[PDB]
Amino acid sequence: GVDIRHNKDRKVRRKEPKSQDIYLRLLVKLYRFLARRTNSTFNQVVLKRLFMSRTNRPPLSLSRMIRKMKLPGRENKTAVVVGTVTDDVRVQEVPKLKVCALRVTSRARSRILKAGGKILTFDQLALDSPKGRGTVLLSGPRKGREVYRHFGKAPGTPHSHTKPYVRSKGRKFERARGRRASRGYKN
Amino acid sequence: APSRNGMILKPHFHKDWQRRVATWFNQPARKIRRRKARQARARRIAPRPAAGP
Amino acid sequence: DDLYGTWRKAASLKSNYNLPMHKMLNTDLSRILKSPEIQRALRAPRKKIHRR
Amino acid sequence: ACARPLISVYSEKGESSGKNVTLPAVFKAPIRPDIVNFVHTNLRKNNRQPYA
Amino acid sequence: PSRLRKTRKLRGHVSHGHGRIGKHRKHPGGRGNAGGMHHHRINFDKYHPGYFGKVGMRHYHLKRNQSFCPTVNLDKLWTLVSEQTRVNAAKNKTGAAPIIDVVRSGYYKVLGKGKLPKQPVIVKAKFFSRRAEEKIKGVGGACVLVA
Amino acid sequence: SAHLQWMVVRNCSSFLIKRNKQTYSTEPNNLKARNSFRYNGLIHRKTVGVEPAADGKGVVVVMKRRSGQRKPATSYVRTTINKNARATLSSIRHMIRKNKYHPDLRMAAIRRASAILRSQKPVM
RNA sequence: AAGCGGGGCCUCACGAUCCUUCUGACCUUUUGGGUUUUAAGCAGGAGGUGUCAGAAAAGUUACCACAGGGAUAACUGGCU
RNA sequence: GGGACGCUACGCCGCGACGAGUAGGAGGGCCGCUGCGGUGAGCCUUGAAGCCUAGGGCGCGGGCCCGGGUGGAGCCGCCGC
RNA sequence: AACUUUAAAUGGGUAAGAAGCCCGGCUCGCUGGUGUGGAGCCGGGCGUGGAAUGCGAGUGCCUAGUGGGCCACUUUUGGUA
RNA sequence: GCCACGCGUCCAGCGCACGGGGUCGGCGGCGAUGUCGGCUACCCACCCGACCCGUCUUGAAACACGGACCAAGGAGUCUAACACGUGCGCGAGUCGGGGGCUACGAAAGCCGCCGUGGCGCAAUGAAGGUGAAGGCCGGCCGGCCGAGGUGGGAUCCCGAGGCAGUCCGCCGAGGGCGCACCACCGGCCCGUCUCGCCCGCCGCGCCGGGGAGGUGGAGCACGAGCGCACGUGUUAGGACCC
RNA sequence: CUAAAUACCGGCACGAGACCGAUAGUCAACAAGUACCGUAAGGGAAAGUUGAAAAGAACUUUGAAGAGAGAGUUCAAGAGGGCGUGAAACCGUUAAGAGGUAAACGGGUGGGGUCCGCGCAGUCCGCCCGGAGGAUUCAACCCGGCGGCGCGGUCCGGCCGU
């Protein structure tokens, strides 16, 4: 008899991506070799993020990537984004950039290359920098989804601002007793 | 019996709706019938435009 | 070439359609893995079987 | 692919004709059997007659 | 795919995933949203605050066509016209400000959310905000009313 | 490419058969008859193939050229060897090792040729 | 004067939605526009559900019926 | 300045620790039935399906393959649905 | 038990550092004998990682079943039991 | 008994083996019409164990209920809505689902000057309505800088050093830019409360608006949704079956 | 007053199916709204299959006959008139085994049958030696064809550029 708990002896994490596409798998096969043969942790973050789900590797807007290269690793340094690199329409000027991404929106490819930039794929990144040397790894807003506004502390609770699940917002759609100080109570 | 978190829903299925159910399997056959009558009308007014006045 | 176009020219018979981009370009990873550029930044392979 | 080959047109007797046509970029499109299997198994449900 | 559903793994199990004490009866809690002022009070307060009661004025014959006043921010103001006009606006030495007709693209009101590039504009719109006007005047533009 | 087409043929291929907890492939150039990346005769640009002769006496060695990759009528050239047992194994070893032609399968062709010559040997 | 007091020295003496009534405004709507009644709104009190997180509610069946309950009685058997 | 095996990478190999179970949840099924799109130059009156079987066996198991008898006309393997 | 001057054992909080000390200086519409007091900002100097032992931790969604319990040492209520 | 082997200057091969999990380079017999072997599956004998299943229950073998036996059938299905997770395509966009044009084909393809319209891209207030950074300099105006900060932050950058003498790469005390995300302090939008100084026009007031400090919002603060499919869960439907 | 877009589980004639296959699918695949039941309103079944072709068993014999035994048809009567395939519950008979704690079961053996291994003289495969043999036979050269590679340090010319 052993007094140990098997409640959480099995760690829950992704070993291989649930996608059945073959182009990601060939990129995954390439980065499994780089993780266990090189000493860089960059090949350990990229390989971990390649397994991740669509909601875990949020799209990265172009204006955010301009903003993070206004405060870069001190200027030639490439950008590595595991998700999709999307275009932003409220940005006016774009500099020349070195961008690595799984997918780039068609307008963003034209906008980056118009400024003299360069777009690389993940197999080209390994040929350029096998160890991730001189790279900046970025990500989109993980909590940027509208789903997270419904999460957290439940509504109808003091200081628990959270969007309720309503079919349509209006004057007679959860503005009564649970919200009005005139009618019953409020939180 | 509601669950932990969810919406308040009003499904309008309290009538005998199963009797009055309109399927749309006539739609691919209806499109042929609309086209054949339109083509037959155009040949009747062959010099006049097919749209009309 | 007119129904789907190349990558630098859109289709002339579709309203708005171009060929999809590639997730990766050099799909033959055997050529990539023994290419010299990776081969410098690799540790020594450990292939001595150490059983119990 | 960077360079695209030159496909030769064949005659009615199996011999190669003098005309040659550049390979379209459509044949260089990515191969995604999962998406093809997704489309094929979904479009086969449209040519189905209802039973009840 | 019925082969991928839960019922294929539940064959041979007596209670079919519904328990032996609390059997899967027909309607133990009542049909629909029963018990708002009753046994389902806590779920109706902890998750749907404000469900019960009336507030506001009634409006008998409301037409949504009358209240149609779409808005656009100063972020996507230059996206309305093509990119060619933006390049030539800063390139032109005479100072001829291009005209962006907001009603033409399908918006009526202009809001001053975003930054404007430093080149003059002529903005024709059905309505304007106060902060949207000062941003346009701050660049050296003009706000033109149109109906 | 070789790695791209392998991910498609690995499960949905007509030459592959699976039964009795085993997996095999019936490709014309798949020596060792196993479904694998190295031994697939159709996948790779350079392929070694060993087949019995048409007349039953000797072995034919299938050689795949690199010129007409999308020209299957020209891509394959076939040479017939009808010499003694030691000299036949010496020639197939020479065509693979000394030409540096896909050298991980040199002994696999030797194993296949050594059994095909034994198969056509007069039966006791 | 420092200070104390927005009830009773403290531990208890009280009430959701909807509806009604009163009060507060140089407040909003009353619908195509304007004026005036009226009506509907915002905010703050009150009119109560004591089964007190709040249904509008008399009996009898020995002519009785149904789903059940040994979770619950009349009998035997058990413990005292 | 002339040489053993390997690697269906969804594969193979090495270390340690652990293995109860009602309700309930999850994962893997080269477990089983029916029909459809592909696929096996698949099986078949020199004998299909079905059924019986004191035989040989395989898999922990769901089950499966051969041997024998009856039977006379269809049936199955793999990839998806 | 509805008394208490005393008063245990068992038990319940807190602390055992780097988010800690020691300096120097700005701001305040807060408080004013007095750069008084307080708070917030900065900049600087101190690592023997400041009890023992053991252990990888933190965190976000969806969620079934359950909401009749019983027995055993010790304490104890009602009841003769 | 000894895990001690050289000089001067200054203060290496051969064999043996308690050695990274067993070998024999050791043997003896019997095997053609009566012998060898055959876990399992056919039958029988013995020892040990062993109460008939399902269900309700704190408690079933119960003197608690269903149940002679066998074959076939026989019970979480379908539509709609929603939530979450996952896969795919596009991406501040996305989508024809309704409508037109070109045996299987009732398919498939095409039409965005057929995107009308659905969702998102802006919220707040009952409503009228309103509707999303500032600072510095010079004299309310004219120029400039122009998208918040602190702490923690995977990753990336430099090199005090160290692997006669240079290059590559290594690692490295220490020093930084800091992704996502968390905590906090600020800033902006709408309603409400309080307090003021004011300015100004096309019709100078019971006018129009700004400011400062609290407070409420399902807000902003360099997007993330749309379409399809799958699974789970909750419902309305006959709704797991009687 | 007025056609078109619209609806159509009745009727006429059609075409089709990722539908079901005689306890399924309409109640009804068949002399089915039939047999049958109730005074009546109404309720309402069960029931497909010899064989390719009846070639449906001539004739002899027992029995009163039903029923058999021979013979004959058929590829097959082991398809013989409710007849294709003929499972289980159940019953009859043959062979084997066993039998006073109802029967049955799990683990471990042992014994007896059943067929099988087609075992009954127990492995061959490579390398070297020996000697017996038998070849049209080796290495090395010449000619022709094919293929690979080349950093030909950069030969020459084509073609393409996500």
Image (cartoon, coloured by chain):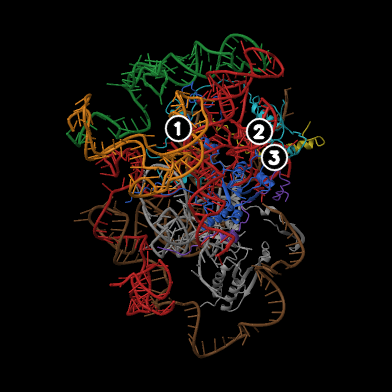
Chain colours: A blue, B yellow, C purple, E cyan, G green, I orange, J red, K brown
Q: For the residue marked with disc 1, what is the amino acid?
A: Ala
Q: Chain of mark 2?
A: E
Rendered position, A105 above or below G23: below
Q: Are marks 2 and 1 in contact (CB under 8 Å)?
A: no
Mark 1 vs mark 3, CA separation in Å: 48 Å
As helix, strand or loop, the secondary structure at mark 2 comes to: loop
Task: Rate crowding at label 2 as few (under 14), some (14 to 19) or many (20 or more) other CA atoms within 10 Å.
Answer: some
> Looking at the rendering, which quadrant does residue F43 occupy?
bottom right
Q: For the residue marked with disc 3, what is the amino acid?
A: Ile
Same subunit under labels 2 and 1? no
* Front-lying residue, J184 or F34: J184
Task: Find residue B24 and report its horizontal and vertical position in percent.
Answer: 62, 37
As helix, strand or loop, the secondary structure at mark 3 comes to: helix
Q: Are marks 3 and 2 in contact (CB under 8 Å)?
A: no
Nearer the N terminus, badge 1 or badge 3? 1
Q: What number is the disc on residue B32?
A: 3
Residue pictured at 51% horizontal, 78% vertical:
F124
As helix, strand or loop, the secondary structure at mark 1 comes to: loop
**Residue corresponding to mark 2:** E74
> Looking at the rendering, which quadrant does residue J92 occupy?
top right
* Front-lying residue, E127 or I63: E127
Task: Find residue K119 and report its horizontal and vertical position in percent.
Answer: 41, 74
**Residue corresponding to mark 1:** B1
Q: Chain of mark 3?
A: B
Mark 2 vs mark 1, CA separation in Å: 48 Å
Mark 3 vs mark 2, CA separation in Å: 49 Å
Q: Chain of mark 1?
A: B
Task: Find residue C41 and report its horizontal and vertical position in percent.
Answer: 55, 59
